[PDB]
Image 1: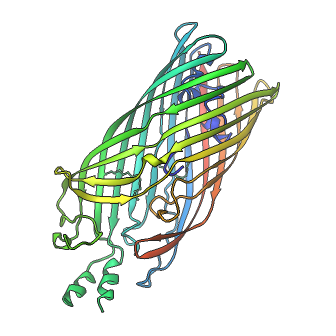
Image 2: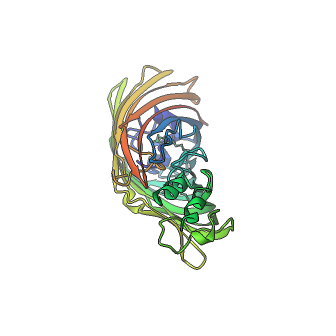
Image 3: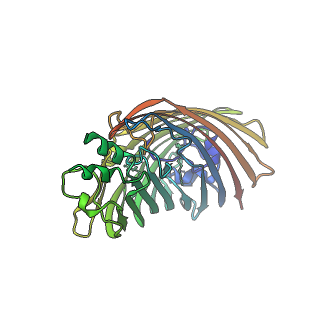
Length: 412
Ligand SMILES: CCCCCCCCCCCC[N+](C)(C)[O-]
Ligand SMILES: CCCCCCCCCCCC[N+](C)(C)[O-]
């Protein structure tokens, strides 16, 4: 999925996030399917983080004749996570979890010649969840949850070398020599803002027996109405001449309004304890990116200041993986998973460098005694190399990523 993230559990990172919401070895999953809450007999707690280490690269040459090579344009990332699960009654349970389901970080140098389309793009998301569940009979459980998302975002763009490109094409003369005076790192657009968003989630859990069980779950859409600073160092004169360029302010910071839709996600999952020391778990996540059509930043007067058309479309994430319950102490796991890109080639962009991803993964849990247990997980996910045609340039891009992750567990 585009700029989506599934690292709520390092326990689950070991399995390619397969069967999640269906598995429940640790408190880690009640945030995935707040139905699992019914699975715990006592207060359980989990905490840790996932180090995401990408390696995305851009390659290509611009008509001006300057490289559009961009080495490692996706910073590392420390995505933490905390969850709590406790029983209220022999029929009700609640829980809370701090996790991040959405984020990005595609950061180009301020002097990249393709600057207009590859500046900086950040998006941090914190999702505080509070949900509860109730068990009808020994077969199914129902759960509803409330999320207060806190998003932090910031978009920047610059005049690539467009200047010299424009100033060339025009070969009203000083009108050229001037746009040749513009430098590579000219704040062509700056946006930023901190805002809260709200959403809900529900999950159903039909469990055939203590060793087999399935689940259907939903995470609502989540809109974020940003009200933040916006500006463009280009001269106001550059305006109203039909250019696709973004509204100029000459340095002036004008209040800006933008809205970010955070795709709903449907997920079906299954978990089986086939053998005393083996269990298999698969899932099929559906993330509706159709909800994320564009990025439009408006003024107080509702007029457009910035607007990039994304046009993503619904996508999915299939996942298969297993766990090897060696013994009271040692536990292992591995999984494969494949998730489809929302971005249709013809919209693909170096900003949201995205292509179909393949998941290979392996993990391990050591439990010192009954209450404690540490989790360690490794995941490597490669993907397809694709051609990107944006604005006046034609880039090429490739992406591979490593993700390591620890997590501690404890139950009273
Ligand atoms: C503050 C968060 C920064 C996020 C860094 C983005 C890394 C994107 C790399 C693809 C990883 C996607 N995955 C694992 C979440 O599914
Ligand atoms: C003013 C804050 C706006 C929030 C920024 C949200 C960015 C989501 C990532 C979409 C990538 C940006 N894009 C379309 C310009 O390439």
